[PDB]
């Protein structure tokens, strides 16, 4: 079963402190359009959030727009690093988020 388009539909977000939760990230991305879903890396063993995650949109343009709209967008007191989830370097991070679940 294919699923390459999905890759084009996901923007990696980093440099997000504990003050910037999905509630805010999604809100930020919301300003760039409707975000299908947004999941980040959360250490269950440490019950603490890693700091980075990925947001999957419904339209490539929307995700791309969010990337260019954000991409190091000041908000977390530093900048919200946003890079295509289909990045070669982002692939390494996704490799961890590569669980595969029925999520819309």
Image (cartoon, helix red, strand yellow):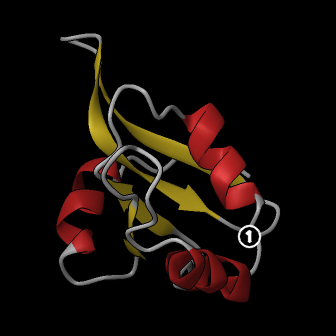
Q: Which residue is mark 1?
A: 32
User: From the viewer's perspective, is 100 left or right of 34?
Assistant: left
In this view, 33 is above or below 48: below
Q: Pinpoint residue 81: horizontal percent, then vertical percent.
A: 35, 64
Q: Pinpoint residue 13: horizontal percent, then vertical percent.
A: 40, 58
Furthest-right residue in this view? 34
Q: Give the residue at x 17% y 66%.
A: 92
Q: Give the residue at x 36% y 26%.
A: 18
Q: Secondary structure at mark 1?
A: loop
In this view, 44 is above or below 35: above
Q: Give the residue at x 34% y 49%.
A: 97
Q: Nearer the viewer, residue 42 or 7?
A: 42
Q: Quadrant of residue 44?
A: top left
Q: Quadrant of the N terminus?
A: bottom right
User: From the viewer's perspective, is 58 left or right of 92?
Assistant: right
User: From the viewer's perspective, is 97 left or right of 35?
Assistant: left
Q: Pinpoint residue 34: horizontal percent, then vertical percent.
A: 82, 61
Q: Quadrant of residue 54?
A: bottom left
Q: Residues within 10 Å of mark 1 (few under 14, many from 20)?
A: some
Can residue 15 be seen in the rendering of this structure?
yes
Q: Pinpoint residue 37: horizontal percent, then vertical percent.
A: 67, 50
Q: Quadrant of residue 23?
A: top right
In this view, 82 is above or below 5: above
Q: Give the residue at x 19% y 11%.
A: 46
Can residue 103 be seen in the rendering of this structure?
no
């Amino acid at each position: 079963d294919p699923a390459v388009d999905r890759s084009l539909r996901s923007v990696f977000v980093g440099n997000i402190p504990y003050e910037a939760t999905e509630e805010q990230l999604k809100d930020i991305f919301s300003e760039v359009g409707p975000v299908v879903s947004f999941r980040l890396v959360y250490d269950r063993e440490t019950g603490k959030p890693k700091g980075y995650g990925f947001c999957e949109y419904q339209d490539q343009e929307t995700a791309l727009s969010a990337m260019r709209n954000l991409n190091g967008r000041e908000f977390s007191g530093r900048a919200l690093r946003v890079d295509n989830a289909a990045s070669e370097k982002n692939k390494e991070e996704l490799k961890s988020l590569g669980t595969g679940a029925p999520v819309i």
